[PDB]
Image (spheres, coloured by chain):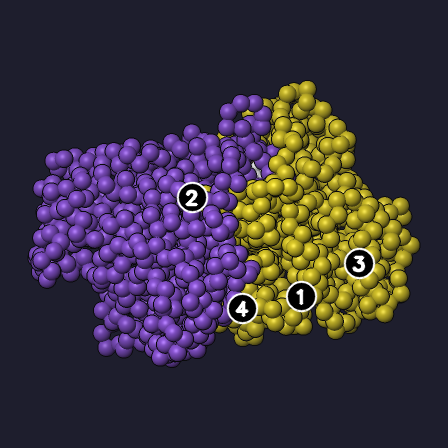
Chain colours: A purple, B yellow
Amino acid sequence: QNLKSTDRAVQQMLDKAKREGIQTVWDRYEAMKPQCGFGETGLCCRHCLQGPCRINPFGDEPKVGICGATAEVIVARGLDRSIAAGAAGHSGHAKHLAHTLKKAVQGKAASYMIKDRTKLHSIAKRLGIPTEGQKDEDIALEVAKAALADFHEKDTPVLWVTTVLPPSRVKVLSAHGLIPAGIDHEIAEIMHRTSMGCDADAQNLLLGGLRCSLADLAGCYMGTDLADILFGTPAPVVTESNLGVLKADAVNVAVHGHNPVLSDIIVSVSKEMENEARAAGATGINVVGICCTGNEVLMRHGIPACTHSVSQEMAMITGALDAMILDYQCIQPSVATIAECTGTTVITTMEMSKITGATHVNFAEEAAVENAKQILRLAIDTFKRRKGKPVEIPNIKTKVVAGFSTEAIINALSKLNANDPLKPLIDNVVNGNIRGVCLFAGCNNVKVPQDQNFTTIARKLLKQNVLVVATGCGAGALMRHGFMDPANVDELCGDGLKAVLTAIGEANGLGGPLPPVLHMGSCVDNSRAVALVAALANRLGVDLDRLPVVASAAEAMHEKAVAIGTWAVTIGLPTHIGVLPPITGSLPVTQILTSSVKDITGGYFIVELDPETAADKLLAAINERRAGLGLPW
Amino acid sequence: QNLKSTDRAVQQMLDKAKREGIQTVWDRYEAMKPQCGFGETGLCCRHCLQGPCRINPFGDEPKVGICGATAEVIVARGLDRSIAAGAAGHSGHAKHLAHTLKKAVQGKAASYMIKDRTKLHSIAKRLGIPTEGQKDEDIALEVAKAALADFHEKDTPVLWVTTVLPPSRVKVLSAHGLIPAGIDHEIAEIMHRTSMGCDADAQNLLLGGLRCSLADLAGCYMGTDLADILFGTPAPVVTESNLGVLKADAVNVAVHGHNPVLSDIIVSVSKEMENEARAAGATGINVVGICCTGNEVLMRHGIPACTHSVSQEMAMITGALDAMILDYQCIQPSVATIAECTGTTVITTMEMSKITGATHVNFAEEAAVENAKQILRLAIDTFKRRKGKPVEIPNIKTKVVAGFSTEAIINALSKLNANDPLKPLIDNVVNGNIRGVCLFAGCNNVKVPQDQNFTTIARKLLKQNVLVVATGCGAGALMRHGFMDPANVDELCGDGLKAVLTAIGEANGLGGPLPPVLHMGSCVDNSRAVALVAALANRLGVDLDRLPVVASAAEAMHEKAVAIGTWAVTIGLPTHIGVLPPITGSLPVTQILTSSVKDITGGYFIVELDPETAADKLLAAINERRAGLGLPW
Ligand code: SF4
Ligand code: SF4
Ligand SMILES: [Fe+3]
Ligand SMILES: [Fe+3]
Ligand SMILES: [Fe+3]
Ligand SMILES: [Fe+3]
Ligand SMILES: [Fe+3]
Ligand SMILES: [Fe+3]
Ligand SMILES: [Fe+3]
Ligand SMILES: [Fe+3]
């Protein structure tokens, strides 16, 4: 079971599902091989009823789509559509948060409120929204209206793009017409231009896709900002991760998905429902996290991460998972089917995200508490049915220090320098103690043994004094293998990095160093690493395509991840992706994305499937940026 | 060449392309067989990097996607995405027209203006925009701002849905949450919910898709209204169609695509460029039409339709086609490749729709004339290169009477009854002289011998006294076979229909009958047939799902067509489609779309690939609606 997952709890539960006869994602993957060469290479198109059209990667006819579409065009249209669908997911989540905020500050959802006034003021001022003499509800109402405004055309471009990148980057992007005019506008225009009989030039297509990926960036940044206003800016926390955070003698309730609007209230209501949890023989309600909603409650409240991504079903396999509460995105629909064998109540809540088989509780921000209890009651109900029956929880769990928002990191650096908090980080970059910065992002993928690319690449980079920050299921993969535990700095980190992590730690009231990897939150919280990197650029007066920053979607899978990789390339970063995107059917497009895009944005894609090789190329790019600053490496 | 096209000019040019060695769409289709069963049935999914996932239609594993997605879900997600991409095309076109209007009435594009004040006033009042005491530029500015507003969320739903259907239909749709909140909002939400890990229930998905198809309806209706304000409401015209409208001794310039913003100005500038056309040995500039832009200039100015859809390349094969001026949608990118053999200047103009190989002229509404000349000069330039060299134009052309907007039709009926213009049409329905109304819509498809389903089904329906109206390439297929020629009423139409077409004709100052098919315009002008059908419903006080109206996408192909079929079902119509949509891999979804949807909207899909069988089922549905009114049949 090692070619499936490098996670030991996951291997134990895989053995269980094998003997109990429950189909897993790896099983469905095994029944899918050998996969379609056309699909994998991108040479498949079904945008009209004359198709499907396939193009042979190598050989005789068909050399071209029925309508005449070349391989360059088929590949670039497919990729543009994945960028747009990612942008739709991130943007829908942030749009929901903006409606939540407007409802709140107009007295419509008393379960919600402004929990971070500093953040709201810094945002409203980033946007040129007047603060002084204006009351908070009016300020937040303005901020929310602006968020909603960024989804359509208007007098200004998308503010959550133009006001969050260094103006030099904004100028570089505006010269090539890359600035989104509206988030949903860009999504619709992608769907227009990639449909049959429209755009038929690969450069033109890919430029459209770069623009749409900045629309996605805006969705991420909006979601981060709005969720921080609404639920508090993450600050460092200590919790634990892996399946061992589940307890047999408690009501175990998993928050799973991406949108914290629901699950943060779940977290807060669960505490008061203890009185009722006891009357069923439970120590209480044990709220754990799966995927990105889980990372959100782990960043804000120290909620332990139970599992992530490709191994989410393994949670239910323990037999101790009483309630799985979904919102949307990255939920394997198999959980519904699986719940009949493991005894779990699987509950959907968002009306555009139901799974056939599941129970649906219609959540709305206005009646939050009334539904939260309704769900948790059901959770305790299921704990009745499984009282005194054999659970198998692998006793595997790790110590996780997380909650490193960009604000937390700037506060952490301030204790070394109160009026120039970025100065110490810059100094240790300049003298080699930090070789560069690498952001691990994205999901697990069934094609890659779970966490293998993440942990391998992280191992080389840490041993090379690269500051590593991580989000979403990247942060999940690293924390489940010890990389968010300060006690592992010694083994993992090279001497200089060790020194800096130690200096900051001892200077922040601990006598111990920061974790070896900085957990920065969920998928939209990739925006946080932009905020930091932008700040870095600004404090040094250069564009991002000169900083020794890189990014790695080491085991990418979802369309969100493609949009994210593309907007890391678009804001200047060298961007590795550890699974094939479907571009290898076109050398011109591959060449545009790994090279000639260098000439437009300074970023570029690094396609490398071997994790050791990928760490080498990532260090090579970091070191090239060093050499461009005149820096030693 | 008869299994390719039932059009005789097209067969002549197919023989030419065969001997000259030019690859055609039928050739690329031949090199694509046998096509992918997975694709054709809808059991293929590539929404994430773990795919591609295929599901065997019948047999052993794979029975399910890697993530767990059942076949019901894969099919409904694919179909939702095609609905959304259609909606994106229609909505982008209308959004462009709304920007054109705002620019015009703010003194920004003097090449454009209000050419129909009656239409603008009737629209502004349909929307509750105040007219009296307000000047026209302010009224149109308000109308345009409202159009732009319907693309995003706001205080009201999409006005170009709620104010154009009978309120009973609006209530029926609002009860099931089917009313769009924003056009691009619905598109984005479709892309969100159909991506991996989100909506996983087929009914929930298909309801989302119904809503998105009404967003597409709104795009069509907006485009029709704005283009009518801007360029005039079509009134009956006489012109000709088929390749024989090309002339060897003139500069032949084809307007091709969907968006008339450019090509209407092309039409108007071409007349004055005669002085320059003569100085090259040309009788002038011979502007013809291809596809829907062509239908727009055929409805408004009597521009002859040269060809349509699957046979567009055949135009260039004559050797007489000097300039092909594209905007976007339904342009086979092969034309670029083909232009090097036929000597045609292929010119793209829209910046999100370029074909590698073509010349791009950057059009903008503000400098319209300056670019139009630039393009036409090039056209005349090419007429120099081909002076005194062998063209083969098939001398095949037909007489076309068209320009039957809903206003033109209501005016035509008024001469029988001035104060109750719909009364005579209703009376002849009620007494059997009109059995029902059938709208032919959509494109040609390479899988069907060109025009065969259209002409066969039209033949049965006309012989059964069914009023037939037609749009886009449906209207193209019928007019190229004589169905828009009054001289064919005798042969085609049954006695009662003949009588009504004759009465209206003789009463409209001709002594001859209306054509056998009412040409109502382009793809967005499907909206016109809604306006009529709605008016009919209103004049009778019933919902559309009780009128003997049906619709037929007899040879559908593009994603636009799927969105259109779905919103004909959603507004109540029985809707035949003469090519397989990719739904047959799921009986539950097929059943939802051909039956259980009856219980939600009153419409339903009729999947029938045999055109005679389809005419039978279309008559059966018309006659069932008759029986529901208590009517004889
Ligand atoms: S758009 Fe072109 S390549 Fe794609 S399915 Fe249709 S005919 Fe084939
Ligand atoms: S979303 Fe599911 S079915 Fe579609 S490609 Fe990904 S794993 Fe396969
Ligand atoms: Fe995840
Ligand atoms: Fe995630
Ligand atoms: Fe993910
Ligand atoms: Fe993610
Ligand atoms: Fe067409
Ligand atoms: Fe058309
Ligand atoms: Fe078409
Ligand atoms: Fe069309």
Q: Amino acid at mark 1?
A: Ile
Question: Callout 3: residue from which chain?
Answer: B
Mark 2 and mark 1: Cα distance apart in space: 40 Å
The earlier-in-sequence mark between 1 and 3 is: 1
* Vertical arrangement, residue A72 with respect to residue B460, above or below: above
**Quarter of the image holding residue A230?**
bottom left
* Vertical arrangement, residue A276 with respect to residue A201, above or below: below
* Identity of the residue drawn at 29% across and 55% down: A397
The earlier-in-sequence mark between 4 and 1 is: 4
Q: Amino acid at mark 3?
A: Ala
Which of the numbered marks, if any, corresponds to residue B621? 3
> How many C-alpha atoms fall within 10 Å of the one at disc 2: few (<14), some, or many (≥20)?
many
**Quarter of the image holding residue B499?**
bottom right
Q: Nearer the viewer, residue A245 or B254?
A: A245
> How many C-alpha atoms fall within 10 Å of the one at disc 4: few (<14), some, or many (≥20)?
some
Mark 3 and mark 4: Cα distance apart in space: 32 Å
Q: Nearer the viewer, residue B603 or B499?
A: B603
Question: Callout 4: residue from which chain?
Answer: B
Q: Amino acid at mark 4?
A: Pro
Which of the numbered marks, if any, corresponds to residue B157? 4
- The local secondary structure at tag 2 comes to loop
Nearer mark to the viewer, of 1 and 3: 1
